[PDB]
Image (cartoon, rainbow over the protein chains, first blue to last red):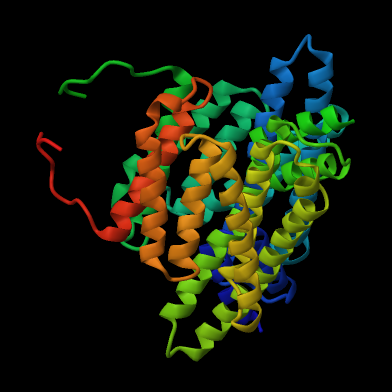
Length: 240
Length: 240
């Protein structure tokens, strides 16, 4: 039965019907067995497109709400619709967080798995934080940081600095500092350290995932360029 | 109340939440009053993106179903999922066709409106025909052709050959002949006549919609180029 669900999930992915895809992989998860790396990635892809649609819509409607200041009639329309989108967004995140607490994190035997799922837990509390309302926000932010931190400690011990999951964790944990805690200095430090540590040990890349590692390293440096304001003029060869 | 619904529909359009958009304009339609040209276009846009998502998914899963011939295990998966998508697709089309019969077509006072809605009726029976199963298909195909034909007769009498609705009707009625009746000769004749008649009376374009007319004329000629196999080599100036 779980193989049928996985194949239908792959079929929904091709059709770009990500609600179906998430439903299929939710059923697989609820069977209780530890997910394979394929199943783990299908669940991740599915719920990143389900929640992503609400995050995109939320940003559009928030922008309209802000640009209709002094137009109370239009701004009330935007505010109420934003709150409708937020409700959908929370239900998705709570759905993911339940699966992580009840099934994925407890059944994670290998270190790679538990970093993946704790990073995922940090992500979906971060998405809740993006739309949180002051009082509840504090607790949501703490839950996100605690998940990121435990994942950070495990991956630092068990993984090479070039591992894609370790790099991807640094990418998102840095963004958490920059966007949620409004701490760009801590965010840049985290991103620079992870990039530097990977550049140092490039010999520890594997053929199975050197393309993924190098993409995430480029994303890390892109965020640094964005956050520090570097570049803008074409470079010419020069020594280090 | 209808102005609030229209504004929320415009808000859903910007957020690309087309289910919401269709729901808003369905409520507006069900109020019974004749729709303005703005409301008419919002309803059209909304349901063309709702049904379009199913048509796109249907084509992906149909292609996988065809490419898994001789792989009965995978092909059964695709077939069943295709049939799930078809059920959603029919419910959308029946929803539109109900609105057209109960509200839009009866309340259409001006000729431009009744051509628009009869063209729309031909479209959504055409979408049903795209997924119909032999016995029911005949009746569905007849309903589509009858709607297109009545729209064709009204627009020929009341509209200039450059009017976007008249041109758009020719574009879809031709595609109906090519794809549903498998009659490329009749399809090309219909498209060429409409293009030629518009080229003849270019002086009858208006500033309010000359860009739309010229786009549809280009679509008409594109289909002709596709269906006759014309072109392929760069042209040089030469007399007519």
